[PDB]
Image (cartoon, rainbow, N blue to C red):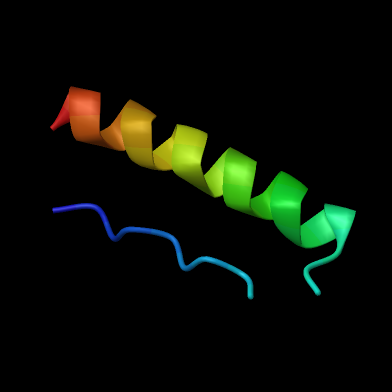
Length: 33
């Protein structure tokens, strides 16, 4: 199963963008799975 991205806990926009992209990737792979 695809891993759940960690919440960056303060956090910079980059980490939010990464968290969002990783979350989207999680949803994509979770649906694919």
